[PDB]
Each structure stands twice: as C-alpha cells, then as structure tokens.
Length: 129
Image (cartoon, rainbow, N blue to C red; front, top):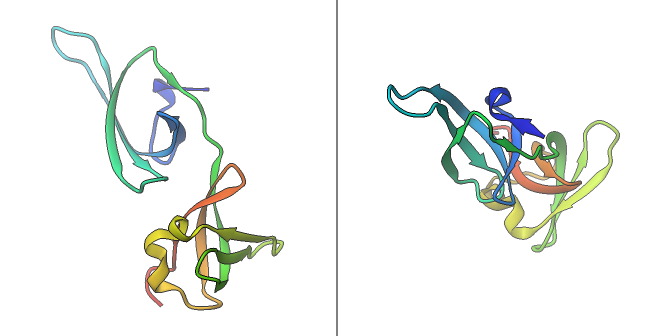
C-alpha cells in the first residue's frame, strides 16, 4: 500500500511480517549504479532497530498501528490493564508485551500505548514520575 517515495519518519509499515515504524529514510544515487533508498526501522514487536534498502520501484504493505493514551490500572502478573483516557475503553496487555514497561508501573499513571490490529504491543510511560 505504501511506496518508497512516501517513506518517512513515523510511517508504519509491514516488514517481513513484522510491524515497523520508520526512524529515518535516505535517498541515494551511486555514481555508476542503481539508485535506491536507505531506511531505518523501529521494529515495534522486538523493539530492535533494523536497516534496509529499496530500489525506487518497491513497496511495503501499510500496517494499522496507533499510539493511544490510557491509564494503567493493575496487573495480575500475566496481563497488565489500561483504559483509553478518551472514552475509557478497557484494554489489557500480555506479560512480555508491556516489556521494559514493568518496573515503572504506578497504579493510575497515564501511559502511551502502541497498538497493532486492535491488540497492544509496546508501553511507554511519562518518562519519569
């Protein structure tokens, strides 16, 4: 759904089956060679960075992913719980899913939540509280 010209920071695309967000994109022409794009991704699943090139033709599928704010409520040790701070819709996350999130949880803190396919991936607090 998306093509190399459109590439840019924050754009969310599907890369090797993984949800990703573009950190930075650089167009380059080698003298003597084919032109192409040097792209860096944040892989929202593994949190890891990765870097890849594309010739001018190539595309990637759009990924539906968005960051919503919710307040952390509680944890059962398995899932962690939130609700949108907009209409108060409740959502829960997998243990791993929250990831590094765990040690920063203050009940009633309002966080930002990375969400793919109506299901949550990553959790980013208000920096420090």
